[PDB]
Amino acid sequence: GVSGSCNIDVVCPEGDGRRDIIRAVGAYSKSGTLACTGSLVNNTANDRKMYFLTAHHCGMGTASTAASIVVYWNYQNSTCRAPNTPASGANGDGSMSQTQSGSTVKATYATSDFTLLELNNAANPAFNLFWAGWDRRDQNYPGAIAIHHPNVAEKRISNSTSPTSFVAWGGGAGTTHLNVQWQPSGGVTEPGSSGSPIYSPEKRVLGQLHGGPSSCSATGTNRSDQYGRVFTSWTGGGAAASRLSDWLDPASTGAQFIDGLDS
Image 1 (cartoon, one colour):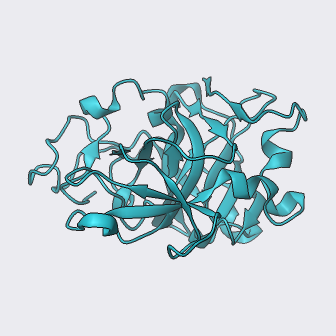
Image 2 (cartoon, one colour):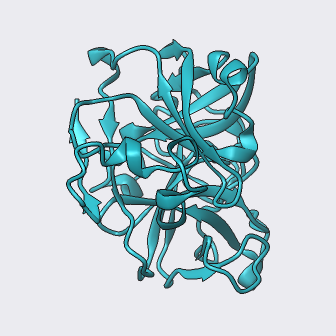
Image 3 (tube, helix red, strand yellow):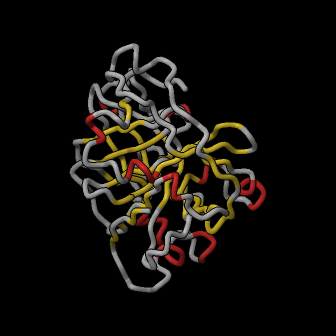
């Protein structure tokens, strides 16, 4: 696939130290057509349940559209293309043969823009999947890591080394979203990155991508994106079908944050 040249292949050194969470992220199609990004999340029972977080606005939060999902794992360029060179903006060499079809909806909620799916098939050992931790504490972070499929093309990583801030979707005062500022020549996100996770520096999911003004040519504060918060989604819309808590802490441990689980 093809995406902006400012984007960074995951096999690049920017991925060092992150090779676990890189394996949590997948691209998917909706009714046959490449659509959005999602990622695996761990839960307190540590049971490898195929909980796949994505964004509500991608339209997977109905029984019918969830059934149509095809997820493509390990879809990334074989070699590091140097960021901001035309090599990075050229068609990549990713494989799309590691797939699984079908899911059900566990919860969906428009305000913090989250859908939790459960994939029908248990993890194939050959796909070497990872279930990432999460952090639901009401706070900001000194930076953040995005792993995503821009234009639903080969997997990329984008780093933020600026503090996050709370916003409402659109950028007004609010607390439902995290605002993330990209580096001035670093990776960004692009259509199809929607639903992709944002991770704290400790590699725990904080939210999933709603959208925002970023592109490889964006300057200043337009080089940014907004992520629906796990904090907000935890309580969500006030019942199991519209929140994360029942699914991610089934053991009622009361955990504020957890780490990941390897396959």
